Image 1: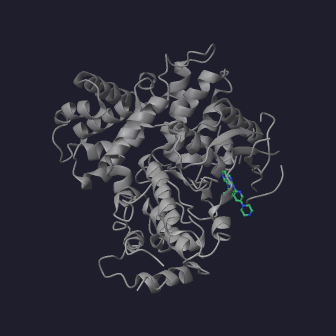
Image 2: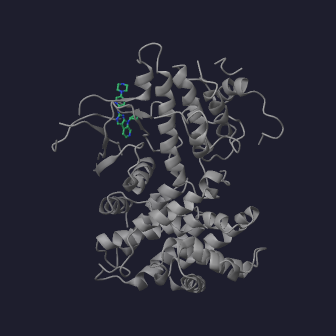
Image 3: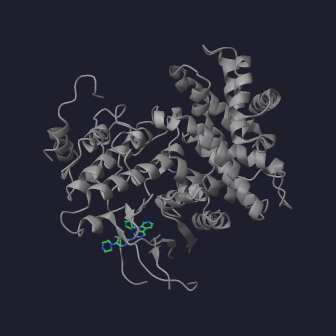
Length: 256
Length: 244
Ligand SMILES: c1cc2c3cnc(Nc4ccc(N5CCNCC5)cn4)nc3n(C3CCCC3)c2cn1
């Protein structure tokens, strides 16, 4: 092990190659609910080898070690040091694509990744998206019970805050928030409580009418991103676009 | 605790049914039930499965916790030998694991031990099943198919809550029986709906009007569908707590 890259997520080499890997030495009711969920999903879907989801290599066991592929940096470090004027125009269009791609993946396998944050999203040297930390992730069957605590404060979709039942649109919320943060290299919504947070939001999207209840350039964006971003932050979650419907939207048609 | 409601992405997207069909092919079809087994038998399973189901029913767990535990258990019992004694430790670990995955409030070690081996032996047995399967624990459960099959069948969306409750229940009890363990998740599920629609007389078509389309949808013959219905209804009917 060398230098920590996550609060505990290490970084080391191996006896096979001194190649780069990420180590997650999980400190252990038996095995923590979350890591069992995380791994279970990742091994379930792994043979599909999707471009946009980190690979896992092994597990072993008192202490526990969880071994992944290494990535250059998290999108957090990226945005915090990308030469002015920050992430370029089209690099932005591109990572939005891969994000919505690895998330079109996921949802189609009835999986929801409800912990979408730039701390979690990864970026390989070649500038490719790798989604990580699948602790809060699980298969969505129907009529199944739900905790009331997913996503870090700043990326939490409304309806979650409103203590309603969530679903997939929870992923698209954070997306149209990371879409936002990317342009303006700082978190778009920075509350302090579930109620402050619902405010920072509600004093932007505006007052949802009686039907949707259980300036935006204001906050350097294309005319087209600003329909996508509005589509991913429509209050009503049965109105929020789907990653599939979004991948096809006009903001994207000009692309590598 | 609030419940997952309809989600077009996750239930009405046609490629969800497709991908279920696919990942269904990632659990290699069992040759015979518990082949690798020298001591315990299928008889020993219907019992333990019956306790397990009850344990899942009595503690009000999500409908998809018992299919996963049955899946885990069988799988573990291809790659490891188990005694007639430990056979209960094992099945109690499967519920421990399966709950942690598919349900928001897991069974605990206390609840699983206080009524049954020690609090450590069980944990070590969670370990042993975790290793043996190399932590590849999730699976495609017969339960996963109900709603996508309801969408596919153009069943009026508002009949889904009752049908989900009825059929997932009929399904889970069948899964106790041996001969249901061979059938493919999609098919076990199709039987569920038909066995159910027949019974309740839900405002659908009559069930035979879903046979030729469930054929189309799952890609089996209208005979395999009928047999899978019959087989399932029968396995339902074979439920008996006094077997314990
Ligand atoms: C599985 C695999 C990974 C993984 C693989 N590579 C990297 N690479 C990486 C990230 C960040 C940094 N920086 C170092 C200086 N401080 C700022 C950040 C450098 N390298 N991070 C990974 N994570 C992280 C998600 C959030 C926490 C752990 C994973 C989580 N699960």
